[PDB]
Amino acid sequence: YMLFTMIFVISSIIITVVVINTHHR
Image 1 (cartoon, rainbow, N blue to C red):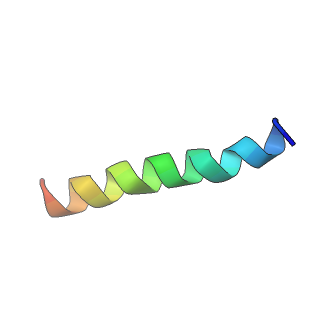
Image 2 (image 1 turned 90 degrees about the vertical axis):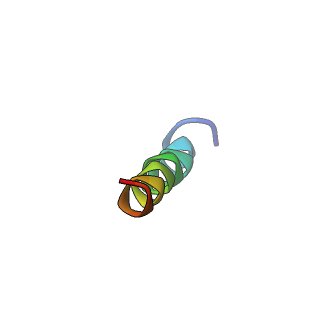
């Protein structure tokens, strides 16, 4: 619904970068 909902993708962006970081230090 184009506000709050977006945070769900925010979560994934961060976590994704966090994965890549944890693996490829």
